[PDB]
Image (cartoon, rainbow, N blue to C red; front, side, top):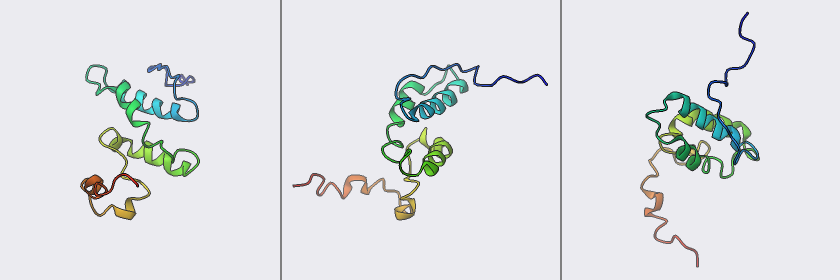
Length: 114
């Protein structure tokens, strides 16, 4: 009996950019989570959420698996701030290895396309 308002009043983050469809939610969870955390040791929230929201959003966001997009991003968000997305869906396809090598070692034989 004393908490009727919301809670996102502490962060008070401005968000007017890619917010077009749901990128707002992305730049929001990325900013509000890494921001409120610490303002002295930020890894570069601005430069972080700006360079990440471009991958997990390639084409899986809404017209794909809104179910997975959310889980993947939201849940794995931890690994997102670290490296990237292990292809939440292709994982089973080739998660047994580290695709850190074949990343280009093989496609380098023929990267272009005559």
